[PDB]
Length: 144
Length: 170
Image (cartoon, rainbow over all chains, first blue to last red; front, side, top):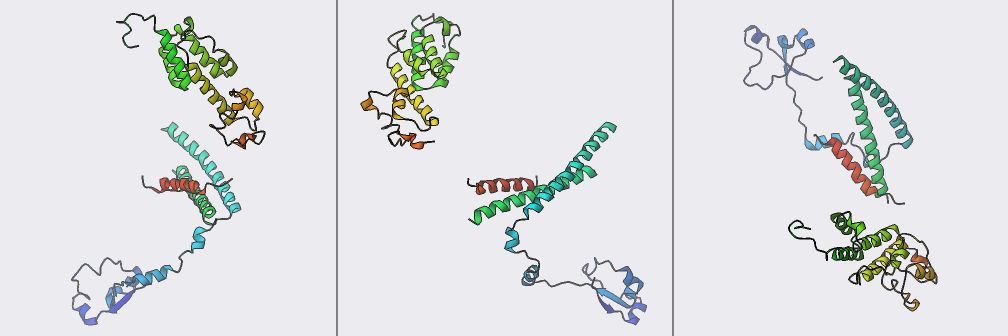
């Protein structure tokens, strides 16, 4: 939340002329803030558009901040924790399977959240298990 | 088989049909042998001798009575069934050798001679000079003892295939 400003000369506004010329569509597309309006955004000053000059080298340096290490790329999750997580999610997915069975049955007999949650659980299970299986394969090959 | 209706019955036919069946036995083409049997009439396989004899020989061979199939040399319906019996003898010895291959850990020379019918004992090295399962005649012949690593590359291939099928937009 940053914003630039410049003042409007007291004469120009009273003269009926707009504070700032408008020769192009650039500059608009910015929604002025309600706080700035109630504090007089256009009556004493006006908001200038802020652009950012991002260089490729600067962006790469910024990426270095949270860039992951090849270690963390090639490392394995704790196996006991992995088994615990798989068991937990599979039990949750069991419960959602029961719910989704009852939901499909009731809806199709009288003619969603269960299906969506079950899809999310299956997605997380597949991604985690596949990632760790492949990481284990790669470790077994690479480290001998 | 083609022009059965127009042509008359050939009395001098079943002899040759059985001869061809015996030749198929000798060459060890059991699939073709059984297709030929299926082509043949059902009644003939039992009524006739010319066809029944090759059928009986294959029956003994596929039952496993190698002694019986050897003993069935004498009953030749006609002299034409000759030298096919000898190729069949070679095939029988090859089959026995295959049994010794896939089974019979640690076999000996005298029992091998008795079972796999070799020629005169001075020629007992036959099939060890040719088939030669690196026998290593350590007196006992040891049968040459003829008969733990993670396939990580293959498993990674499969897992990457799963990931590909999950991540493709389709």
